[PDB]
Length: 48
Length: 50
Image (cartoon, rainbow over all chains, first blue to last red; front, side):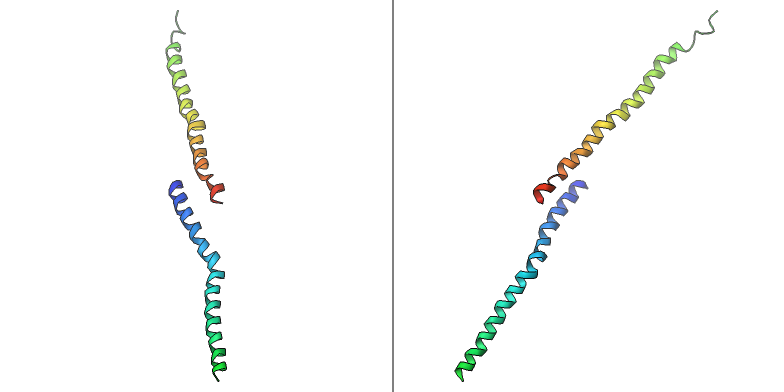
């Protein structure tokens, strides 16, 4: 199982990067979604 | 005349067995242990993965 541990470990640690990166990446997608929605509302204000 | 006839026959066989018991222990000292170190050699992809 030292070999099977080696296999699960490389698998785990690369996957773990997903949490390490998405704590800032997921944040970005939402920031982009927010700006999109915000720009709309100001567009509507200009429609006034 | 021969109170010391015995012993010599066993000495060759016994010396052999005792040696052999160690022979088995000996291969463990290096073959099994280096095989264990092989596992470290395999583990020591760690630096790459790091």
